[PDB]
């Protein structure tokens, strides 16, 4: 740690903190000295929280990484009611399109139309 | 206005009065006239620091287009500001306008990774 600080290599220091499981320090270094990796660090931390079975905090960090559009539906694909609550909470257009595509494949066309109308996906 | 009239009445040989005018004009948040003074004296480094510190990015860009040696001093701070706003396409163009072509490449490689 001292050597990486002496080199001013905040990128290798961030990778080091991640590998050490010290995620808070890793996020602090990313927020102050390594801002270009900050989205990737949130994504990796969210993956380790998901692996640790903490889905609620994984959601918050997938949101911060802006990867919630594809990672959240993947993670909650086994728990459909929680995914529905989430889609209704974020009110995001892209998520309403994804949930409407899921309803469309399941044949729930009246509900798919409702969510495509919310998503303003006239096509 | 009085420091301007004095600095316009002063001769180019009177460095100590002119630098005292330029520092008071900087201290009195009058960067367009501190700039005119640093330009009259030919201290282009203090001028570009003045425009970057007083965040006059348009006056900075106009100076950097006139004096290509300051493109780095202007666009590195501005391109960092674009990258910190997650505007990485604009930041990559800004690093390129700075002459920092290797960093304009490395940022896009890092985003690709």
Image: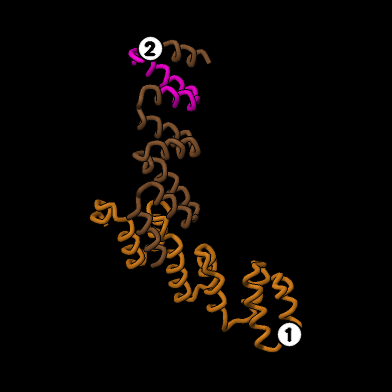
Camera-side residue of A47 and B103: B103
Q: Which chain is brown?
A: B
Q: Nearer the viewer, mark 2 or mark 1?
A: 2
Q: Disc 2 marks which residue? A: B11
Q: Which residue is at the far bottom?
A: A107
Which quarter of the picture shows residue B43? top left
Magenta: main secondary structure: helix
Cβ–Cβ under 8 Å for marks 2 and 1: no
Which quarter of the picture shows residue A80? bottom right
Specify the segment rendered in magenta: B11-37
Q: Which chain is orange?
A: A
Q: Disc 1 marks which residue? A: A109
Q: Position of residue B80 (x, y in %)?
A: 43, 49
Q: Which quadrant, please, contains the C terminus of chain A?
A: bottom right
In the image, residue B76 above or below residue B30: below
At numbered mark 1, what does the secondary structure look like: helix, strand or loop? helix
């Amino acid at each position: 740690e001292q050597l990486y600080r002496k080199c001013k290599r905040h990128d290798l220091l961030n990778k080091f903190y991640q590998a050490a499981g010290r995620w808070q320090e890793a996020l602090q270094v990313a927020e102050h000295h390594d801002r270009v990796h900050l989205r990737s660090t949130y994504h990796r931390y969210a993956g380790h929280l998901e692996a640790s079975a903490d889905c609620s905090r994984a959601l918050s960090y997938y949101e911060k990484s802006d990867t919630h559009r594809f990672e959240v539906p993947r993670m909650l694909s086994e728990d459909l009611p929680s995914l529905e609550l989430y889609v209704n909470k974020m009110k995001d257009k892209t998520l309403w399109r994804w949930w409407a595509q899921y309803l469309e494949s399941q044949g729930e066309m009246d509900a798919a139309l409702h969510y495509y109308e919310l998503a303003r996906d006239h096509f | 206005d009085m420091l301007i009239d004095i600095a316009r009445k002063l001769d180019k040989a009177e460095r100590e009065p002119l630098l005292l005018c330029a520092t008071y004009l900087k201290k009195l948040d009058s960067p367009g006239y501190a700039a005119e003074t640093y330009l009259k004296m030919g201290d282009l480094k203090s001028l570009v620091q003045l425009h970057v510190e007083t965040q006059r990015w348009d006056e900075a860009f106009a100076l950097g287009e006139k004096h290509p040696e300051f493109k780095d001093d202007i666009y590195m701070p501005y391109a960092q500001w674009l990258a910190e706003n997650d505007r990485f396409e604009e930041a990559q163009k800004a690093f390129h306008k700075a002459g920092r072509q290797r960093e304009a490449v490395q940022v896009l490689e890092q985003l690709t990774n």
